[PDB]
Image (tube, coloured by chain):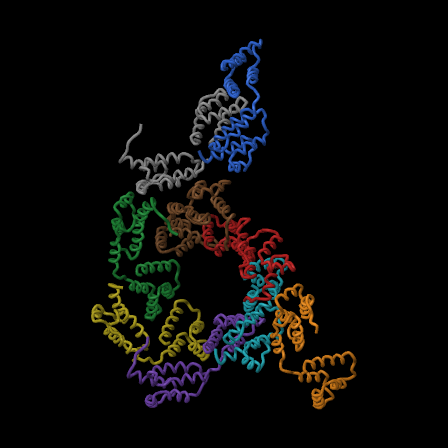
Chain colours: A cyan, B red, C brown, E blue, F green, G yellow, H purple, I orange
Amino acid sequence: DSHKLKNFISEIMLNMSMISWPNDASRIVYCRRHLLNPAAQWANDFVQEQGILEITFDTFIQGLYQHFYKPPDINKIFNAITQLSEAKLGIERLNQRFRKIWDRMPPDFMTEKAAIMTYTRLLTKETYNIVRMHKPETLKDAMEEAYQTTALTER
Amino acid sequence: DSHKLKNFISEIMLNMSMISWPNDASRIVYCRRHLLNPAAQWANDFVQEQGILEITFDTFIQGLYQHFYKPPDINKIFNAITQLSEAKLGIERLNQRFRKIWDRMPPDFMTEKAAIMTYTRLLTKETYNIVRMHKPETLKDAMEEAYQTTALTERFFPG
Amino acid sequence: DSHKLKNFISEIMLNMSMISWPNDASRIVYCRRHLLNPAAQWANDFVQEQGILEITFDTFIQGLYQHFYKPPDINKIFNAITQLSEAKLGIERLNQRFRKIWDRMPPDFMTEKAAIMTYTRLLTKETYNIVRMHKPETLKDAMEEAYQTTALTERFFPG
Amino acid sequence: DSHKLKNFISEIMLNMSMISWPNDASRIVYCRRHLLNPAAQWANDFVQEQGILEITFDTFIQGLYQHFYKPPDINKIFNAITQLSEAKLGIERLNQRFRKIWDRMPPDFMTEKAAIMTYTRLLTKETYNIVRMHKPETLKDAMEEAYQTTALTERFFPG
Amino acid sequence: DSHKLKNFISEIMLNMSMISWPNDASRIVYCRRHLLNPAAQWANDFVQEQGILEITFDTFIQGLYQHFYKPPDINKIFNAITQLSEAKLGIERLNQRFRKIWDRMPPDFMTEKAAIMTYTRLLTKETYNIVRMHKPETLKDAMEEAYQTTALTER
Amino acid sequence: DSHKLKNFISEIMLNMSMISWPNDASRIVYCRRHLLNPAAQWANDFVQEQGILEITFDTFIQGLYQHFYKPPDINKIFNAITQLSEAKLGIERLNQRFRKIWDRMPPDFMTEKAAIMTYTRLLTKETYNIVRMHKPETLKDAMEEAYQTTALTERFFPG
Amino acid sequence: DSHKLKNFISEIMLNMSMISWPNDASRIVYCRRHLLNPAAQWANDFVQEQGILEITFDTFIQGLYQHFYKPPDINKIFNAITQLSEAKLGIERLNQRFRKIWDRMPPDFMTEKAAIMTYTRLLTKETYNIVRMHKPETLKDAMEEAYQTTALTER
Amino acid sequence: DSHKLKNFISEIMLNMSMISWPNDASRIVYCRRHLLNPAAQWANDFVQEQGILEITFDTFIQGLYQHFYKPPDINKIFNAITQLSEAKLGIERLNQRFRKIWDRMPPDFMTEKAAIMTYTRLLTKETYNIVRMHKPETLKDAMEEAYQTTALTERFFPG
Amino acid sequence: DSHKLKNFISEIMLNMSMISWPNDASRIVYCRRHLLNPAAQWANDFVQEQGILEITFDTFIQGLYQHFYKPPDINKIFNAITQLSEAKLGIERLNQRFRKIWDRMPPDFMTEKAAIMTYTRLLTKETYNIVRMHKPETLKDAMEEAYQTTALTERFFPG
């Protein structure tokens, strides 16, 4: 439920972002309309609890953030990661599959170098070569590099 | 159908609650739009029956309340509970299946120790052993313990 | 055609009801737009026949009411009722089947005792015994009693 | 026995009513004379049981009321009604048979249209045709019509 | 002879009761006319014995009461009670038969609960069920209940 | 296709008639939206052919009139009518079959008495008797009468 | 592309025609929205080239007319016309087939009498007879007449 | 996919350009609506990745540019060009086939004389003769000349 | 050589840190004394290269930091870790083997929870059970727990 919910919040925030809002009170309330029943129930209670007009949109999202917490299911995520080999047709499958798995469920997981070691080891030895020359600093860069070389002379 | 319907009414009422309504007539009618066919059919007939403009939103919900509710002491839940054995592949099936059945339909059912006795008896004798050492106090803890030991040295994930 | 038409009128009337109308002439005319061809043809003729600006929305609906006065001629319902025997597996089939048939099409049919006599006679002699002790006053009570005794020491559930 | 008995009491009470009685004791006793054996047996015992001169005429009738007037169960009457088909030779059998069954035991049963639907459905399809043209409003009219057409171009007489 | 005689007295008393009597002397004498020979013989002697005009109608009936009352034998009554089973067609036979037997011959017999236990045990197990729900407090109530349920729905 | 099309045009024209139009160009174009594919194809071509802004709504309807003047069909309808005898099981088949055939394809055909003569002659001599007593004035009344007498002392139902 | 484009312009012009426009500038611009990429590219360039607010809707359509009308190959159209005989089942095939071929590609082709001579010669000798009595003045009338007689006693 | 995509971006940008935008946030988002599924998937992820309200419309298009701008595969185009011989039946096949291949994928390729040398060499020696007398200056002229001589004393037509 | 060298630098820096230095020149030079031959050779050259009195102690250590840079080890370490299964006889082999591999080569590697996940997953499912009840917070605790339960109720090897 929680992974979808994290996505849900981002999007809603974006939609709100482009267009102009005339005041904060309207905006905090508007969030409530999209929500699903237990969350919606919670929302009512939270609105009551605050006797003030509101306390900002961000505060309210943080109560939601607080709401959606899984116990750390690190094993499932590790296991998911283990499954991918290079029998997955080319870069594209891997990149999209990895995105879903990785992005969903980390609270802070492992450090930046570690994330690159895990991502990189999985990749064909050839692809590590080009990507090494010159190196990515982040997982998005690694993924963008591998896809770009494959995609450019293909796609 | 009735359990979902009770939830449905609550939510609808909430949605309505936050925002402002300019008059009652609109509001009573708006309820009709969300409803499903037999209920919707009933609704039309009820609207006709009242020759007045309306009689309040609450009245209309009470006709719905009247339409479907479960009586107290519903054996169906016991029977549902009886069906599960350990032929259900591992913890995961049982935990999810039990959640649906148990969570739906109790007004106050039975006490906390009793709920643990019923949940626990169902479980493999082996699993009761580990779970015993050290004990859960609530049904969520029992369920979390059994799943965690199985899941940890096993498992896959969602998304 | 007539049963749908009775529903159609109710709804249309409701839609109209919530929002405000500035004058009657517009409202009577607006009804014509939704209608289907023969009815629509009739409508034109009726509008002509009245040389006055209009005579009220209600009058016009009454001409429609008149156009299809009562949907059943009590026969089909009796016949439907006749069909059920006790070859229908147990209470559950009968209760659900009877609900559909009975609830649909009565304007006022027969009196309360009569409805219980017809419902009760149909039931197995055994079931009448328990139900007699102690008696139902309404068809819903009879149906609830028969189902409850069968269901309690038996049954399964929905969702 | 009970339906006749309820009639019997009413009449007896009426006869008594018009003329003057000089005292209650005579009147209570006089009731006993008309009664039939088991009831009469009961009566003797009841008179003994009351050591006082009497307790009023009404009290004694209430013991009789107690003795047989029970609320009727519609089922026997429905069942009776069910038995007739058109294998009963012509109108005459049906009309007389129906009279006995129907007239005995209704407190208010079912409404007027319903009574005509039940009576009419039973009749041959042909006879419904003539009777329809032009319609009866009451069960006596239906019965009179069916008999009259059959009788007129047929029949014999009593005495 | 005595059981019939007790009935006889009641009736005679009733007949007398409705209509008016102009004086007591006539009334006491009139009783003598209906009576049968030994009793009638006794009556003559009693009338002589009283040198006064009369001593009241009631007194004279009490001499008759005195004449007839003999001690009963409970065993015949018990034995009578024993005979009934449920081979007697339905409630009606039993109720009428029991009335005759029970009502005749008790001076004080047994207590109220006991009388209900004896009456009730005899009845079909089914009938005890309905009658139990809700209970009779007296033998007349038990008898009225059983008859009413049977009677009401049919025959 | 043509009979429905003649109806279609009338209705569309009516709908347009009640409300106000601000200019002719919009109105002529709006007709195109409701139309079905071959007709719609034609419409495009016709719009092109006229280099002027438009030539009136009526002109455009006349091109449609022209399109479905009629194929020879009165004969087909007569022939269709001829086919029914009383070998068709009872009233129900005939009434439904006749409805389809008759209702489809008349622009004005024959007069009201004539329509009753054709309908009535077809019917069994017996049924004409009851229906005569008392007479129908319209084809719907004749059909309703014949069905009602048969249906009442007989019948089953839909859903 | 050009035949469709000629149709496209006509229609667009019609849609515009019925409803009211408050000013010319809006109208000229609105045309651009419906157009497809190369044409759309051209449109941008043309709008720039005119430094004035606009020069009328008609002018802009003429640039489009200019775009599409290239020289047509009259031979192909003649050849197309030659192919039809009376082996085409009845009027309906011919009329529809002729419409497509003729309507597409003429800038001014041949004169009105000539167009009737070409259309008429193609038709069965019988049909020319009825159509002669009384004559059509335009190709649409000829086509309507032939179809109407066939269609009426048929269709 | 990439060639179409480059066109797609240009156009979208143009449409946006003429009319006024009230703020950047709306505009960046609006781009997402037109896009096709994988690209759309990417878009969602990119929007999330930027925690700020947005970073400009242009930035977002650059991520798309990044996604599928392949160098035009000059080799593929050359290779395509190589395949045609004069075994292709006459001018018509060649002209249409060449149009597709050539027109798609050049950013600036080669100069005008070169394009004529490549086009001309491919053609039958005979056809070069007539076309020479008198010469084409552009590829469209060469193509038009060759087709016209063949077509004129030959040919068929479209529609 | 590099791992020891990183340790060496830290320590030297510490020793220097506690006590006071009167000037930077002395301090930079003093570092040279502890160093081993190739590094020492480098040092001389570096001192010459700087014509200024010195550039700070930190700068000089950075040249050393620069000197260490080996190709990355972490892969080898992961691979080493991968090799162990439970085919290694009991706890003792694993614990000692893991100690060597893990302790050597991390600069900061991964976080504390991660290190426990990697250590724990490797262990037999049974051993995770006891160790879970009650949990270790550090890798030394996990290792001590597993060894203690095995060791306590076991025989140890003589040498």
Q: In this image, C53 relative to I52: left or right? A: left
Regarding residue A16, the answer to whether it shows in the image is: no
Q: Residue F3 lies in what quarter of the image?
A: bottom left
Residue B135 appears at what percent x and percent y? 64, 58
In the displayed structure, E9 sits above or below F97; it is above
Residue H86 appears at what percent x and percent y? 35, 85
Location of the C terminus of chain E by quadrant is top left
- All told, the count of numbered labels is 0
Work out which residue is located at the far front of the displayed protein and give it: I158
* Between C121 and A30, the one nearer to me in the picture: C121
* Between I71 and A40, the one nearer to me in the picture: I71
- Residue at 70% x, 74% y: name it: I159
* Between B2 and G38, the one nearer to me in the picture: B2
Q: In this image, I70 relative to E31: left or right? A: right
Q: Residue A83 lies in what quarter of the image?
A: bottom right
Q: In this image, C84 relative to I138: left or right? A: left
Residue H148 appears at what percent x and percent y? 32, 84
Residue E64 appears at what percent x and percent y? 55, 16
Regarding residue C129, the answer to whether it shows in the image is: yes
- Residue at 31% x, 50% y: name it: F92
Q: In this image, A114 relative to F66: left or right? A: right
